[PDB]
Image (cartoon, rainbow, N blue to C red):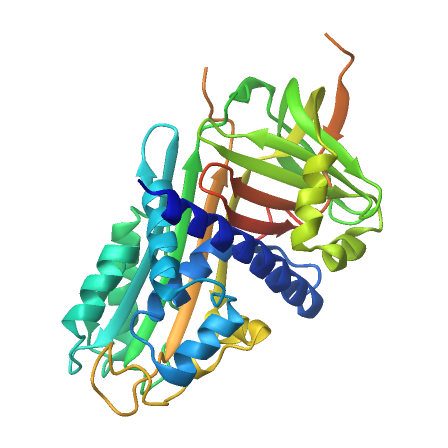
Length: 367
């Protein structure tokens, strides 16, 4: 039985939810007017995986920053292994992979125990690279990742600092069928208001059907859920005019559970833009938002990864990628939910609890 693993996953999912909202708040504060697209879950797997090879102050700070402190470490790794194993699929309904690749300088010797544990618990791999040729190391890493993800995760690395002997690449892609397909013949170019006064034409999908829908008077936003065929849900959060900043600032762990209380199944005429979203983050910068930096410094804390005095993670990048289109399986007067102005998007795994993706979409066709 995997009861205990399932309980650990439930606690870890609450933690990625909080992490996602904290990261979104900080990212939106420093960079307003930009799309933000990342996977709190995928980011968490990367640093939890690093806990298998980290000791002392570096280990303690990752666990403090990511709030991995509530359960024993054995349960932390068993919980993440369960989440990854359950979500990892290449079926007609769902294609999801969480990649964790450490690229280590070929002069270093990654330790067997760490290699085995990372592969067994996270499906993470270590690839030897020649960091003395930075240009070639970048092409090698980008080609390795593009080949592994079948062209879903491309150009992951744009720069490698000299002296880097260890680079972490974390990446997640998603393809899923909706529980009910949208008819592509009904998809049309429609106005997407970038601002109250300024608009761009975007491919807008349309379907009339039964959906979990609601309105939050506290955060002044419409909530709409569109289910995928597998137990995953696309949650659209549409702020009222001039309430986006209020919505971002009000986001909490309790916010989400409150949104769930406001929903009911109703007939809705839904208009949703198609998306092909990617988000790329320098994790050294992103993790400063949760006070995690020792992993990026030399402290003699990574000997379990490889013996070497000055060892640190030189660089770490996260890339999240998702396609949202018509693909899927197959009363009362309809409500109308038009997603045609800046919105938040949460891709939520219901069965294996987790926030797979969190997005702030200011422009669905925006790069």
